[PDB]
Image (tube, coloured by chain):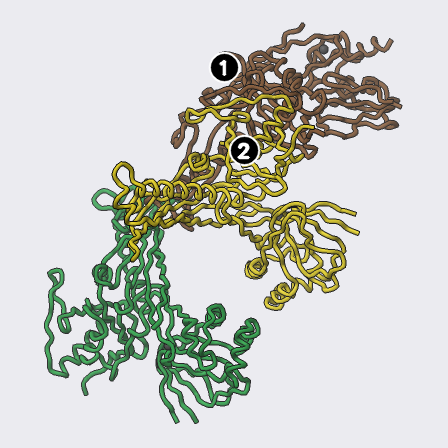
Chain colours: A brown, B green, C yellow
Amino acid sequence: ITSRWLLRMLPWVETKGGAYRVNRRLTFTVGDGRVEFVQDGSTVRVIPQELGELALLRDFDDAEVLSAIADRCVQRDFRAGETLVERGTAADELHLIAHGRIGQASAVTLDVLADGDRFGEHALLDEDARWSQTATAETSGTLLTLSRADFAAVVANSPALRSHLAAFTAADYELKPREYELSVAQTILRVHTRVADLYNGPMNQTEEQLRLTIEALRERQEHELINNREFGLLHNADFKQRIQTHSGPPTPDDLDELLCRRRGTKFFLAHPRTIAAMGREFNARGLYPDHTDLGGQQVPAWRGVPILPCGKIPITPERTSSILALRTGEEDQGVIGLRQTGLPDEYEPGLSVRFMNIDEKAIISYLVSTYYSAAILVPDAVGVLENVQIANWPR
Amino acid sequence: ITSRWLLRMLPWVETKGGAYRVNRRLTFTVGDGRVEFVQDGSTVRVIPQELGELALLRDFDDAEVLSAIADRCVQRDFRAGETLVERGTAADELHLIAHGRIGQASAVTLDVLADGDRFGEHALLDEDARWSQTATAETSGTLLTLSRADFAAVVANSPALRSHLAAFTAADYELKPREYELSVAQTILRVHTRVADLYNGPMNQTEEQLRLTIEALRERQEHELINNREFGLLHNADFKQRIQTHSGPPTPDDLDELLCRRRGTKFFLAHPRTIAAMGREFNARGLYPDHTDLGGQQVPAWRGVPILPCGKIPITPERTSSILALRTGEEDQGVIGLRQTGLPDEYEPGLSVRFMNIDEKAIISYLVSTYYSAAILVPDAVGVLENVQIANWPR
Amino acid sequence: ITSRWLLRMLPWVETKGGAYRVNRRLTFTVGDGRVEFVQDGSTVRVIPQELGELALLRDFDDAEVLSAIADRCVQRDFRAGETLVERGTAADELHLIAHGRIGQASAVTLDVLADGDRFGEHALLDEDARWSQTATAETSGTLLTLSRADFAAVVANSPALRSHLAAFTAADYELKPREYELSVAQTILRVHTRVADLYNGPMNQTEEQLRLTIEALRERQEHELINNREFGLLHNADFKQRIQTHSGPPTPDDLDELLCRRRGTKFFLAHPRTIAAMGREFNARGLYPDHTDLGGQQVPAWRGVPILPCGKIPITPERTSSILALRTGEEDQGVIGLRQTGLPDEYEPGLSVRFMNIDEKAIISYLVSTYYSAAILVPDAVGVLENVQIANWPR
Ligand SMILES: [Ca+2]
Ligand SMILES: [Ca+2]
Ligand SMILES: [Ca+2]
């Protein structure tokens, strides 16, 4: 029953056959010390050529071997405050950082690794490798893992890798399309025959129950568009577009930085608590931002970019939320809503309600279905500001 | 396949939402020795104020206490010839007679209690009470029971009742609406796909089976209108309107008395055996009653009031039936038939047949439903003559 | 004669029969440590199932027993600074906090209980319970009380509760409609016959007195809409919607928080002294808010939400007031004004003036009547900021 800003602001394009295709250009360079990954929503995998940045794998340019090694890595997720390695334990895994920040404490906290960083190089070759530092994850993220045994098996499979390893011991264009499949929000409405036969004259309680079902389906659509893992702006956003706050509260400098990373930002999405925190920061700084009108409706804005509240954005137990800055459009490469209309029996242009059967207990069943998904045409269309402290008050 | 006189004679009114409301006035007096009850079909309950007729409860006019005591009584039914109490057994229950006649035989048959009579007064207060007479039920009826333990608990709950009991030891208008909910006659018609695909050209065996189903539903409607317990003229009739025959056969004096109790009686309903017995009585008395025309159809009548046969009126094993005298109308306060038309898919104005599903065995299922009920606007609209001996012949 | 902003801003809906019905959904969870209540204006009562949160009543799910226990609690109001319990006095009452904050000082001020908190658990079972802490009420509020004797009586009534107590010693959907009855503002206008016979040519002093009467009735309507106990936005507002100021003066952070709790807030209502205090806070912070136009009339606003003055909001002797943030509408679930037009003799669409009689002293009497009430469709439509210090100046 709440406002669904993402549903009414995202343009909707008609897919054919319940599928969409997005052509991706992935520019990457070899030798800059940072590994680039391919992200399909929440699942990520290392580019086989990028893997050649490895010191023990430099100058190896055999597509088969690199592809096999890339396929043999395992994706892992780490939470905030979780310890990945401890001093003294033998090192046997190569860790490539895809997202998040990991503070490494030596025997003296050395530094903090970030996206594209590596630790566990020497563990691949020799068995004497031992973790001499402890890695504590300050922020949640993903991580690719290459085991020593798997690497030894891959070496024993390909003679060329063996020979190169024995010898060593002594902008690239990659197009790979991304396919989006329409997800479904489905439900079954059970209406008793008595409720359909009698309560139908001045108002249809069947029709009112159907309206409630449709509202619940739309709320689920918004919740999935925000929080789903396969598609969904929070997770299906480029790892480079996710920023961390400079101080923790959503200061206006953070909003300026969020507007810096992309051209023609359309709007901000944040929790109402986050909007209250931003207002508190504005009052502390002493500046009063203007309000702009969209669709004949006035709304708070920053630098003329409207800030829209969304209650479906999760709030962590540590009272930290995230802010989304995103541009929408098809002619301008942005974020589009994939949806198929023209269903066989539409109560609503995007909906389909169909009679299923009548049970022995005289209960009619209806199937209410809608098909939806989200696509991000270019990587720089959704930016996420993370770990925004929303429980800060002036003191 | 038989004639359904009640279905075609009762006027039908359209209920909204499958419910009807009847406003009841219940005039009662305190101190006349007879307790008045509230009857909702076959379930009856004593008026809390009427309960103050009790000698040990006179002058108590606390609504809470009387209401609690009234709620704590239990309804019981007794059959003809059943013994309720026996001499020697300790008395522990207060019995309020709601219907029927009970002959009380002392240590010498004292008399016969009837509707509104009480026995078991002294049993409420003291534990020494002992049944010194035997009560044999000559006629079936209902009876309210108040246990000694329950009364002691109610006394121990309310201090005011205690104080009044300790002290004693040394026309009223009550409006209470009655709500009628539409009952349903439902059935499932299973038609094989072969019978629907082939046998459909010159006549539809599916349509003939549906017609048979509709006829069975109408017969069930009549049987419920006569014999059902919640609604139904035999049971949902005022206890004052039920009369007993003077001699046992349906003599014309009994018909005159049945016509006496209400104004503008519309018709009589009786079993064909009962009509034969009435004809035998008429022949014995030597008078030949006239016949009147309703709907262009001639029918036997008494005093110009048509007598209609109904085979759904039960015949007891002792060969005793009952006769119903009833007036129908809405402008004239009488008996109406509650029925809702305008169903979503009507083969007939009151019917609804809907396709359910087709089974794996290629059997189509149809749901045939009709909604009906009966309402009696005023108490003096249905009178019942009971224990009519129908197996009497001249000798 | 003052401006009545609430009268002219609240939309008015036509009730039928002088009554309105609001369908309430009350989502509650068992085991989260907070008890949920049902509020009908100023009278509140604990949910029987919520009462099962009690440690000694956990896992008891008998509707009769819980309903009885809930009915047997007593509602109490406490003022600011009032001491409820003192150390040393034996504990005999269970206190469930419905509103307000209560600071508990042990033998060391432990903490401050708030809405949904409980103290007095152990007092229910044993008679040795003694208050060992003193509870001082910092803010006015309500409180449910369950006495030990009443609980013992309820235990002695139901055997199931006994058995469960002996054994222990060793999201839920609840729909309950709320009914609103139209209140009446009535008065008698006494006009002398001389004033009606002579002073009627160039102007009617009778008509001017009637106009003054109508103005007084409208002022009383506004005062009741704000301050009445049964209906009225100050009291008939959800206990969760009432907030406390962070510092005491109405700082802009408090206004941001007040706008945070609900979507599409329509306007603020505050005393003119409160508006002066808010302006002082704005000047201290150095920001100058914009002004918006409603009905062709310019008005001060915060974040585009107009701030309207209302002199009917009480000012406490401690110079503390309250602010109301509220959205109005029927299509958008908000606050509506229940009012019935089409009266038998209307001088004004909502009014009814009728001649009563002429006294022996030649004084004509007129009855001026209007019917009004207020309804809040959803709980999150009126928010109240309380204890706003309005006598603070820069120093
Ligand atoms: Ca690289
Ligand atoms: Ca009586
Ligand atoms: Ca709870």
Disc 2 chain ID: C
Closer to viewer: mark 1 or mark 2: 2
Q: Depth check: give the residue in front, A368 or A8.
A: A8
Q: Amino acid at mark 1?
A: Glu
Q: Going 52% across and 41% down the picture, which residue do you hit?
A: C379
Q: Which mark is residue A330?
A: 1
Kindly identify which numbered label has been placed on residue C31.
Answer: none
Which residue lies under the disc numbered 2? C272
Return the residue found at the far top: A171
Q: Is residue A191 above or below residue B281?
A: above
Q: Are marks 1 and 2 on the same chain?
A: no
Instruction: Identify the element where label 2 is drawn.
Output: helix
Counting from the top left corner in percent of width and height, residue B116 is at 37, 78
> Residue at image x 73%, y 56%?
C86
Q: Position of residue A275 (x, y in %)?
A: 60, 27
The answer to whether residue B351 is seen in the rendering is no
Give me the C-alpha separation between circle 1 and circle 2.
Answer: 51 Å
Of the 4 image quadrants, the one containing the C terminus of chain A is: top right
Label 1: chain letter: A
Of A219 and C340, nearer the camera is C340
Q: Nearer the viewer, residue A35 or C311?
A: C311
- Amino acid carrying label 2: it is Pro
What residue is at 63 percent from the left and 59 percent from the top? C146
Task: Residue A211: name its quadrant.
Answer: top left
